[PDB]
Image (tube, each protein chain N blue to C red):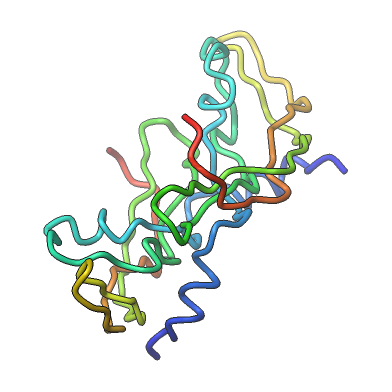
Amino acid sequence: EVVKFMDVYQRSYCHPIETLVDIFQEYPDEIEYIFKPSCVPLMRCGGCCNDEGLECVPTEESNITMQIMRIKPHQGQHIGEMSFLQHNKCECRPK
Amino acid sequence: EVVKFMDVYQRSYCHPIETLVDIFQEYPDEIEYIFKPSCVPLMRCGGCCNDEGLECVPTEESNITMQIMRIKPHQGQHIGEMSFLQHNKCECRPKKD
């Protein structure tokens, strides 16, 4: 089965897609705690635009809260709520 | 609603996930041509593993064929087949790098 040009185009065009995101790229300032899982499923703008001068950026955003196991090594564990940015809408705009 | 711990874990664990890949990452020597679209949807290994000494790697791979428009600048365009590597199955395996 060869993927036809048009649905390659439609499926790849700039839009929100579930992205597995490292928690440390979302909370770089965390120094004490270890997180499990280390990564989370977040709806994020991805894909391509119809000109190389355009770029795929979010226009709408909403926050999402997830249960994450927060570990202080050799000290203890607790499951807590953490908030992450998600993209509801995306647009191809100049760089 | 708040996503349950177990749902986060199952959805984020090392597995094949649809990934938007730039054609120029898969064919870096072909930048004399312009490809529309410039990125394609590929099933690739992604997500996280339950121990520091583990990485998420493919264990089964296959090729997918896609119709892509190839532009030779100021000459013409051609829609032709182009093969891309897909990951069919993934596992957390001891690091090897």
